[PDB]
Length: 24
Length: 24
Length: 27
Length: 27
Ligand SMILES: [N+]
Ligand SMILES: [N+]
Ligand SMILES: [N+]
Ligand SMILES: [N+]
Picture 1 (cartoon, rainbow over the protein chains, first blue to last red):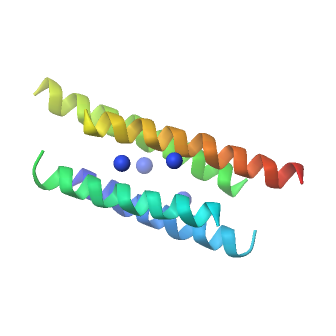
Picture 2: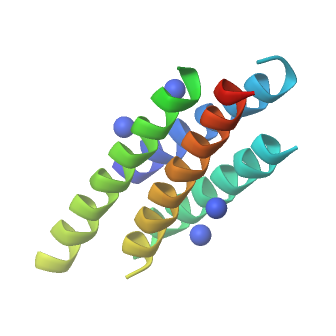
């Protein structure tokens, strides 16, 4: 449910932070 | 580096939220 | 800019989690 | 309790990300 959708958002953010690390 | 460690923390939280969903 | 926008999103998720926690608590 | 503790952690990470964003900006 809701908490699963939030967990998916966190995993998407985790990928963004790793992309920022490796350039910006 | 730092941002990778934070991304790992977010992925660990995502797993906690999914565990909370499926019981608590 | 991007890190600041992600910081806002995480604070917003924290609010959302407290609302969920409360709804469960209340019920 | 647990969701509230995770909410605090996410707000703390948001602060940490703004500090990082700022350090990069400043440099
Ligand atoms: N995001
Ligand atoms: N946690
Ligand atoms: N969100
Ligand atoms: N943290």
